[PDB]
Image 1: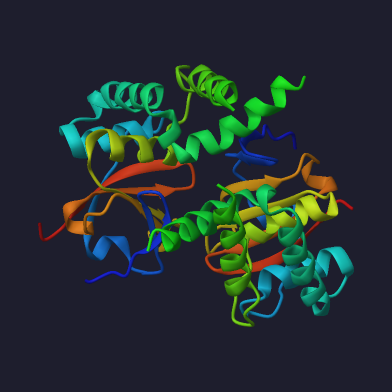
Image 2: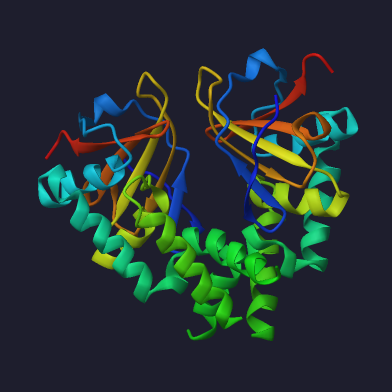
Length: 169
Length: 169
């Protein structure tokens, strides 16, 4: 059960451990729309999918205030912000604006960039297990330093996220 | 036929188009060792998987010269360098050296970090189709701006990469 985690970015770890999810977790399906990541985390953290919007507001509020710590989102949007200016205080400002313009839309697909913001915003550990259709682990990453049993575990299959709860606990 | 690509990183696109690979591509199997990504790309690009080593050399030589454009790999190795140092420019030089120390080993598993390098180094588009074990697409990434029929298409099933050729051409 002891898993070796290697450092992969700020507050971010990966592992090579390969398991079948169903032998340790119960999977809880959430609604298949563009908010599934927010619903899955809201289900584990607040015990209901219906708080996805609070989860989403928490993530975006954290970005507004700690943009320099959203390495996933800023990696994409700060790069793209430099390439509108020629068309370092003020690029990263514009990158945050571009991110917020996308993320505030109703159609936005939450995912791994927002998992990083929630883990820091709430001081929790979020594990994202990427699986195939047979629920076999293709890879796993983890924002935060807690162990898998002390963490909120999410499963990704292609574009869709669901929640996982550990069986024995 | 027409896929809508979402920007996902610098020169990196994603899509949730869902297909069966055998309906559009013939798949060409390459040797199943840690060089299979290089072998898959060498098969499409140079018509032989035995130029995998030139492909690898292309990717790593590109990284030596363009480390700051190697967004996937530099995210990992620049962070590891800056935590080695605690125990903006000295960091990234160390990060590249850490990357090369892993990547130049014969046992290194090439993959998306090097797809990004090859796409920029050679000015081509590489498409990575992640499939489950029955070859149904889970999701797909594209390094570069060309369309699927003008790109080098690679299928990935867990850790293993093979080449894809489009049936129509």
